[PDB]
Image (cartoon, coloured by chain):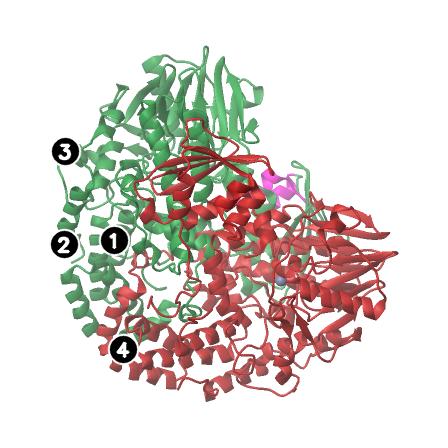
Chain colours: A red, B green
Amino acid sequence: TTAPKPPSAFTVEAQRRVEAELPFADRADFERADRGLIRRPERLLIRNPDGSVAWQLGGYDFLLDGKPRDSINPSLQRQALLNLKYGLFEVAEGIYQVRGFDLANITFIRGDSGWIVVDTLTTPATARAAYELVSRELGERPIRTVIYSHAHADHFGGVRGLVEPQQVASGAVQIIAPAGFMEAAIKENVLAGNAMMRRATYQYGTQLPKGPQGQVDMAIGKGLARGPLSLLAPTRLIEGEGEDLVLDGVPFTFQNTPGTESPAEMNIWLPRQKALLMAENVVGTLHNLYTLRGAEVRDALGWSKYINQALHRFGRQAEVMFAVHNWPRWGNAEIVEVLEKQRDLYGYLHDQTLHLANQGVTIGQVHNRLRLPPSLDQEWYDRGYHGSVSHNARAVLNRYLGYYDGNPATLDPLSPEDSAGRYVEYMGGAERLLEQARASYARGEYRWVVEVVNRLVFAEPDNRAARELQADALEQLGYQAENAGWRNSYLSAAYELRHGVPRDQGSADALAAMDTGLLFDYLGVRLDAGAAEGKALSINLRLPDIGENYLLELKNSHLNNLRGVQSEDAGQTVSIDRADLNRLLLKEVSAVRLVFEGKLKSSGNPLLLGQLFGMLGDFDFWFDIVTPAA
Amino acid sequence: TTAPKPPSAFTVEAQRRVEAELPFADRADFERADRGLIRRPERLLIRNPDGSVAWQLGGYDFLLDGKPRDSINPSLQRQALLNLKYGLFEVAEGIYQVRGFDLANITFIRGDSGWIVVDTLTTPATARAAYELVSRELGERPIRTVIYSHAHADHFGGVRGLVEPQQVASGAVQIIAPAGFMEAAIKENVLAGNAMMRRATYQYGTQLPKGPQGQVDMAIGKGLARGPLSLLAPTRLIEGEGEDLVLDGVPFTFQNTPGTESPAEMNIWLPRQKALLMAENVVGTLHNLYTLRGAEVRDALGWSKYINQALHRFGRQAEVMFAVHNWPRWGNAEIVEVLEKQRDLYGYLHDQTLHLANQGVTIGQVHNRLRLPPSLDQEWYDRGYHGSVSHNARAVLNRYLGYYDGNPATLDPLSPEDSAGRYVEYMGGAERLLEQARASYARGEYRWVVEVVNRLVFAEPDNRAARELQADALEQLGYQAENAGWRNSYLSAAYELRHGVPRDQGSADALAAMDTGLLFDYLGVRLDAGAAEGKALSINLRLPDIGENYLLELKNSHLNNLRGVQSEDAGQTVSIDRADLNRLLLKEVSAVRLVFEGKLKSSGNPLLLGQLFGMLGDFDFWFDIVTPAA
Ligand SMILES: [Zn+2]
C-alpha cells in the first residue's frame, strides 16, 4: 500500500530502549525553556508580501499532547516539544530573545537609546514579526546596531525585515560581522547549489506532511521559514582574534572562531550582566560537522579548542549562557560543565575517530564502532539531533583520508545501476530476492533490507514490490531515528519511492554580493561540453560601476575568467556595467535593449558573447535519488 | 595457485585498445627527455650512512628492452621507460637538473660565485650523491642558496645531504621557501599518519617486487628513495602573491600558488635564461587532487587559475619550461599550448564534475560518465599516471558534497563484515556464489568480480578459494591499469591476501619542528578511552627553551592542550624543555634521569603526568585492509 504503515513490534521495543537507558527523569531543559517568557502569542501565522505562508506552527499541535508516540523517537519527541517553547523571552538586564519565529533566534539588547540586534532570522517577514512583537511588548525602540553572528542564511536572511539600505547609508544604523563574512556567506552555496538544494529537500523534508507520520522537528528549529532572501553588506568587521567595543553605551566583547559552524563566526560576551552568547558552536544539540545537504567537512578540533578558549576567557565570570539556536542556561556551574562537555564532545569525536582510523578502521567501519563515553553520552545537548555521532565520525575520517576505504575492490566500482543487474541475477532472480529480503524485514533487520533491496530498486526502476518494500523498510528506520535529518530523509525518500518525484515544482542581493570571478566560475560549471568541443574564443569585459576588468578565454571545452587583465589581440571587447549584467543573467532584461539604452558597448566581433551564452546549459532541480534516471 | 598468473585474452585485448586510440606515433617526449644529457652513470647505487640501500635502478633493466609486455599498461610502460632517462641534464645557460636520483628532481642554478639549489630530495644520501656528480662534472662550487619549491618530503627531505646547520646559522647559506611552508609541511601527515602510511604501502608498492609482474614506475618518478628524513627551517619566506629577488647576482621571480600540489607552493621564473620552473603544478602527468594514501582534497579550481596567471605573466616570454618532477619543454609555442591544456584540464575536471553533480550524478557514478575531451585526452601530460580522471572526479564531488551519495539506503549501512554473511547466504552462499563469479571471471567482468567476491572475502576471512580468486581478479585489473598507484595497489592487495600481511615488519627534525599544540593533539589522538574514562586531571606545563606555556586538561575521556594560559588551582605543575620532552617522547631517555640531571621541575602532586602517559596507547602499523581483523 502507498500509505504510511504503523510501527513494528521491533520499532516500538527500540523506542522502549531509548526511554530505558538514556536519562529523561531530568526534564530541567523544559524548566529553562519556559522560564522568563514574556508573552506567548496563541496563534502564530507570519505572511509574505506576495501573500504566501512564511511560518506557521498549528501543524505541530499534535505534540502539545504530552503523550508518547512510537512512530517518533522519544528523545527527538522531547527536542520537538522544547522547540515548541516559542515566544518572547527575558534573559538579561537588557537582554531579550525571540524564539520559534524561525529556525534561528534573534537577540535584542537595549542600548540606553535604541536596539542592538543579533542576526535576522531567514526572511524579512519573520524579522518584521519579531520586531513588531518586541516593539508592542516592551516599547517601540529604533534599531541602531545589527550583528551578524556568522555567515549562514538562517541568521542574515531577513535583514531588510529590520532595516533599509538608506538607514545604513546615512550612518544611522551599524552592521557588524566577523571578518571574512561575505566570503563565507556565498562561496559554498553556489557551484554545487542545485545538488545541495535538491539533496536538502530530503534532509529538511520540504515534501513532508507535518504529523507523527511525517516531519516533527529540525532540532535546532521546528523547521526553516520559507520566503525571499535578503543580505546587506557589513559596515564594520571584527578583524583579528576579537575586539572589545562600546555601542549605544553597551559593552560588547567579540571572540572570533573561524571554522566552527562557519568559516566566519564569533562568540559575544556581555560583561555588565555577565551573559555569554556562544553563537552556533554551543547549542542544544550535537551540530553537523558535515551537513547531509553537502558541504566541506568542518574542523571539529578547532571547534573544541575555540569552545575551550571561550570557557577560560568567559565561563568563570559568565552566570548565564545562551545561543542563536535554542535556549539558555543559568548558574555558572551548569555553564562550565556544559562548555567542558561540549568542548570534550567534538574533541572526543575528532580524536577517537582518528584513533580508530589509525588502527585501520575504514570509513565503512567506524560509525558502528565509535560509541560515546557515559559522561557525554548522558546529557541532552550532546544527543545527535542535528548532527549525529555516526555521520560526523565518517565525515572526520573522510576529511583526513578521503572517501577511499583502502581496499582496491572499492577503487574502481561500477555505477550501482550497472552492477544492479548482476546483484539481482546472483541472488535468485527478482522475486526470490524479495521473499528472503522480506524474511529479513520480518526479523527486524531494516538497515540491511534498505541496502540490499536498493540494488533491485536500481535494477528494476518500476518494480512496485521493490519500491514500496524499500519504502516501509526505510520509513521504519525513519520512525526510530533520533536524528531529525535522518528521519526527514528516510521519510522523504519513502514518499518519493511510493508517489514518484514532483513533476510539477534566485535572490538579487546574493547575486549582487556574489564576486564577478565566482559568478563566472559558476558560468563555467553551467557550460555544455557538447557545444563546447572544438571551438575557441577570447572575450574582454569592462565593468565600470565596479571598475574591474576581466578576460574570458575558451579552449578545450573550458571557460577561463581572469580579473583585471586583458589582451588586445583578443576576439571581442565588451563594455557593460555589473548591476545590469546581473539583470541580464537574472533574466529581467534582454541584451539588445541594454544596447539601445546606451550601456552595452561592443567592439570587434559582436557575436562571440552571444554564442558563449548559447553554450551555457541548465540543471533540472527535480532529479531522481532513490531510483536511476527515468 | 599463489603465484602471479599471465594476462588474459581480455587483458591483452584491452592493452591493444590502448595502443589503438592513444597517439603513440609522436615519441617527442623521448628526445626531450634525453635532451641536454651531460653524462649518464652506467651503474647507480646510492648507500646510506647506516649501510642500507637508498636508491638503485638495476631492478628496472627489463624496461630498457623497448618491447611491449601486456602484463603492464603500454602507456604506463612508456611513462616508466621515459622515467628511466636518468642522469645530469642542461636546460639553459646556467640551469641544470639531476633526475632519477630520487622520485623528485634537484635543480642547480649557476650563481657567478656559487650554486642556487631548488629542492633537496627524499633523503640526505640521494642529495649528496647528486651534488658530488654536479661537482666532478662541471666543477666543485659551494651551495649558498637553497629553495624549497613547496612543502613535501620528496623535495625538502634530503636538505642535510647538501648543507649543515653550521652554514645556515652563520648566514653564509640561505634557505628560501613559500610562506606557510613548514606548517604546511607537517600538519598533514601527522594525526592520521599511521593510517596514511599503511594505506600508502599499497599506492607506492613497498611490498612489491620490481618486475613486469610487479612495480614498474611511480609516474612522477620510478619510485620513492628510502632513507632518513631531514628538514631545516626557512631563513626567509616568500610572502604575498610573489617576490622578485637577486641571489649571487642572479635574478629570480617567485610566484606563490597556495592550494596546489601543496598548501604552500611557488612557481619560479628565471628571466636571463628565460626559463619557467613550475614546481608541482605542471608536470609530466595529471596530478592527484586526492592521493589515495589519504588526504584532504586539493583545490583543482585554484590550481587551474594559478596555471592561467603563470601563462599570462610568463608563458608569452617563456622559451623553456621545466618542473620538479620529470622533464622539460622547449619552444614557447609548445610551452603555451601545454599550459593552456594543463589549465583547461584541471578546470574541465572541476567544472564538468560539478556540472554532472548538479545534474544529479552521485559519487558512485561520476567517474564512469565523466570523459575528457579529445584535445586534452590526446596528449601525454594529461594521461592518468599519478592522478586519474576517475578518482580525481569523485574527490571534487567529495569536496563539495562529501561522501553521502544522497540515497538514505546508503545513510546508515552495516559494516561490510557484518553484512558480508548475509550477502553470502542469500546469493546462495559460499560455493555457488564462487562458480557464478568464476563464470563472470571467464567473461572479463573483472571490476565486477572484485566487488562481489570481496563480500565473501569479508564473510569468510580464511577462505582460500575466495581470496586467491579475488587476487587474480584484482591483479589482472592492475595489469591493465594505466595509473601507477592503481597498478601498485591492485598488486599489493593481491600479494597480501595471497601471502598474508607481513608479520615481521620517527624523524627528529620533523618532531622538533612539530608544534607543541599539534604534538599534544597527536597525544590526545593516541589516548585510550578505556583507561581514560571517569578520570579527571589538570597538568600545568612550562617550556622555557621555546618560552611557551601550556595547560593540559582531561575530562570526559578527552585531552585538551591550551597555550599561553594556565590556571593556578590546577592539579600539577611541571617545567621541562621542548628538546628533552622530545627525547622523552621519542624514547631516547627516561624521565627519572631528566629529573636528576636538573631539567625536570615538578610542583604539586607529581604523579599525574606519569598517569596520563600511561593512558596513552599505540597503533599497529600492519593492520588488515582486504580482510577483516584476523
Ligand atoms: Zn542555523
Give the quarter of the image for residue B532. Answer: bottom right
The residue identified by callout 2 is B10
Residue at mark 3 to residue at mark 1: CA–CA distance: 26 Å
Where A26 sits versus B581, above or below?
below
Circles 4 and 3 on the same subunit: yes
The residue identified by callout 4 is B426
The residue identified by callout 3 is B65
Residue at mark 4 to residue at mark 1: CA–CA distance: 29 Å
Chain of the residue under label 4:
B
Where A329 sits versus B288, above or below?
below
The residue identified by callout 1 is B495
Circle 4: element type: loop
The residue at 37%/83% (across/down) is A441
Circle 3: element type: helix
Q: Give, as a three-letter code, the residue at label 4.
A: Tyr
Q: Give, as a three-letter code, the residue at label 2.
A: Phe
Residue closest to the eye, A159 or B539: A159
**Front disc: 2 or 1:** 2
The residue at 35%/58% (across/down) is B625
Residue B581 painted magenta: yes
Dot 4 or dot 1: first in sequence order is: 4
Dot 3 or dot 1: first in sequence order is: 3
